[PDB]
Amino acid sequence: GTLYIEQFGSNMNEKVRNGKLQGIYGRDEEIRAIIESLLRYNKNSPVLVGNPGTGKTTIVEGLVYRIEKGDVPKELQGYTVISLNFRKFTSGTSYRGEFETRMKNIIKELKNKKNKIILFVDEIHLLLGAGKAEGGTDAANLLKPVLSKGEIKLIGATTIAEYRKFIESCSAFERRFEKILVEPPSVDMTVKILRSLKSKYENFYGINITDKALVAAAKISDRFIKDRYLPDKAIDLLNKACSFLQVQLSGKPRIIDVTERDIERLSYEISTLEKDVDKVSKKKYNKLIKEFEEKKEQLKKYYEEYVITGERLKRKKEIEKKLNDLKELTQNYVYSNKEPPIELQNSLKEAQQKYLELYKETVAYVEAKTHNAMNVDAVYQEHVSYIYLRDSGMPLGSLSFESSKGALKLYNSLSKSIIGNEDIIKSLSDAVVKAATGMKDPEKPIGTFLFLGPTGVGKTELAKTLAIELFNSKDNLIRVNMSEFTEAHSVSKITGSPPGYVGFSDSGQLTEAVREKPHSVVLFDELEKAHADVFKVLLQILGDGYINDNHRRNIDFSNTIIIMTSNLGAELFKKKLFFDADNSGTPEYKRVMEDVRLSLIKKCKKVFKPEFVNRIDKIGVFEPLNKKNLHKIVALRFKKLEKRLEEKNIQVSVSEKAIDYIIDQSYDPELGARPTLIFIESVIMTKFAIMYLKKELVDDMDVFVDYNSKAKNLVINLS
Amino acid sequence: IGATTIAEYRKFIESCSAFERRFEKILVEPPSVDMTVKILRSLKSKYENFYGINITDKALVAAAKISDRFIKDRYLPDKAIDLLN
Ligand SMILES: Nc1ncnc2c1ncn2[C@@H]1O[C@H](COP(=O)(O)OP(=O)(O)OP(O)(O)=S)[C@@H](O)[C@H]1O
Ligand SMILES: Nc1ncnc2c1ncn2[C@@H]1O[C@H](COP(=O)(O)OP(=O)(O)OP(O)(O)=S)[C@@H](O)[C@H]1O
């Protein structure tokens, strides 16, 4: 067959006869349209115009598969299909005959009936650059008069943008090529492709793929990605699964490599005999000894559980001979029974009492480990998301991986750092609970909130804690300084400048930054100070993820928690100072608060244009702090001084008098206990941070704070 | 058995497209430098003789690390030969 190729390019049909091209899944309407456009009275050149993820190139291999197998009309039987550019982009670099040997040996080969070659081009827009030289015109312009003949046949495929920029610019080279649009396949069709490739991956890779992984491989990638079109994403995620399981399950798992290093390299070298004196910094070296003891729990526990999951594997040796073989040996066409009460209904109970007990425990190990599941050959749905979460802006673990234990303790962990208004937290934490499960809204962004409240309470602090907990980083916190966006002209800074104006290279300040981190909270600082035109864009933001850039690409605001604090604290309701600073009088506080909250909602109609209120999932009024609440906050702020300022050895303690001294002095109703964050930095931190002798510098800080209540600073040096 | 360099055969030797399947490859490896130090210890037997100068073994071990770090071309085992010369 090399006589017709002229040994550049390749015949497709010989590769079909080799074991290299199996049967392509049905794109039955798309292929038969090309067969009609190939047999024609003139111009004989279908082009697969379509998206980059269409798989149009593969389709042609499905057509060649129909050529060799004979599912084609009689006029098209026996043709050889040849791709043109495999040696180089110029199909042969000549250097002896610079125009004779290549262009004339192809067009001459289109001759009489026994020459049944069919040309094929991978990208037809590179032909506009082919033959480009100072002394010679493009090879595509030479093929333009050739296409008015019945002997030439061409099939090509480009992206839509390269079809616009290159093919349509010539407008006569555009004309003799027939459009056949390759529509991207629907969501259900991408599932039907992956069911064809189970026999590929379970034979050529050997790993098993559950059907729960197949449905998740399409549907997770579709709603969460708005480029690199559909059928590649359903296939490339499972192609990442073929390399993910192969490196690890055949060899040692990754978790053994991580717990091994920590105990010996840093916690063992510092614990040695080098400093037994304990005179310089006597508090610190007591803690360095304790660090070695807990790290013994790392090595021993996972090793035995690896045997326990390894115990499941030799139960998998047993099911091969009983559940797999006994169905495949006795059950045949000869009378189809072979005494079904013996050995055959017993095997049905073996499917229930051996396999399903193995099956449930392997399923139960999926919620246990949630990624890098040891001794587990089947692909699972949570491992499919783990491959996606590698690609998205996620750490290796922050509370989305830790399903069904971390999501419920997320309500407990937010109650640690933030104290009041747990009913808002119940609405806040359950939105994460809906996101962690299949209770997901594909249009609406998950967790939109409107944080009205008095000035001074920790409203914006929740967005800091969710970035530290749900996303393990302050990078996923995205502040929006609405004080920059007060003007009516400032609204273009959100979505970027429109085309033809100053800028336009960036898609904007906020809208660009969400594109690389779709899993991130979106903080809006203070919605009380903005022009209402800025609110007009926000109607789409809370409404859908259909936010377009200047280049009009969608931005994925799914999995974005849109926190929108705004004060209005000064204006009225919570502005009225809680008359009774009681913790919560149930017959009083509960009744009056809702009456002000209704008013707060009523006020919104006054200003936030009540269309915007319908987009809110939960308006939450924060309760203003006083002596009962403020007494409980401040000790956790000293615990924030415990975690940050130790290692350099600071471990504070508080008393009955140590909190009472702060509350009667630093509480201001007009500022709403804001200077309680200043009274810490302004007077006791002056007793800290000194050069020498007013603070123990490196040695120890085990101080127990007390005063004689004399309205003067007396730091009793008990440290 | 024949031998051609890595960057060349992609353009000219692979041109025949049927010879290329019969042009099976042998991937000559990156040197694994620390085991090439034993090569220089053997080859000094002529270099101590032809130059008449005794060569310290402690110097040639550091000669590999200079070829590793300060210079980043010429396919490392060629350099440790030249720095002895
Ligand atoms: N109908 C189908 N049957 C079998 N496999 C398919 C089908 N559609 C897509 N695929 C797979 O998805 C891939 C699609 O390949 P292409 O998209 O042609 O890649 P390409 O040749 O680089 O051209 P691009 O990427 O579209 S610009 C192939 O490797 C196929 O394995
Ligand atoms: N419920 C709370 N839980 C934890 N810390 C709190 C709480 N209320 C207030 N704080 C602390 O007090 C300060 C609150 O900061 P924020 O009030 O959130 O800033 P802000 O929200 O812009 O304030 P306003 O009300 O808009 S002026 C921080 O130092 C918090 O740590």
Image: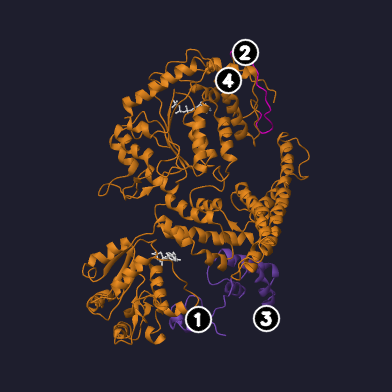
Chain colours: A orange, B purple
Q: Between A652 and A44, which is closer to the camera in this rendering?
A: A44
Can residue A701 be found in the magenta stretch? Answer: yes
Amino acid under label 4? His
Name the residue carrying label 3.
Answer: B46
Report the residue at 45% width, 82% height from top.
Answer: B17
From this view, report whether residue A587 is shown above or below residue A393.
above
Q: Which mark is residue A625?
A: none
User: Circle 3 sits in a helix, a strand or a loop, which is it?
Assistant: helix
Name the front one of labels 4 and 3: 4
Q: Are marks 2 and 3 on the same chain?
A: no
Instruction: Tell me if A496 is positioned left or right of A205 in this view.
Output: left
| Whole-percent x, y for residue B49 in the image | 68, 81
**How many numbered discs, if any?**
4
Name the residue carrying label 1.
Answer: B21
Q: CA distance from mark 2 to mark 1?
A: 92 Å
Q: Which mark is residue A709?
A: 2
Amino acid under label 1? Arg
Q: Are marks 4 and 3 in contact (CB under 8 Å)?
A: no
Name the residue carrying label 4.
Answer: A631
| Whole-percent x, y for residue A627 in the image | 55, 17
Q: Magenta residues? A: A696-711
Q: Are marks 4 and 3 on the same chain?
A: no
At label 2, counting other C-alpha atoms closer than 10 Å, the crowd grade (few under 14, some 14-19, many 20 or more) is few
User: Circle 4 sits in a helix, a strand or a loop, which is it?
Assistant: helix
Subunit bearing disc 1: B
Residue A463 visible, this orientation: yes
| Whole-percent x, y for residue A230 in the image | 41, 57
Name the front one of labels 2 and 3: 2
Subunit bearing disc 2: A
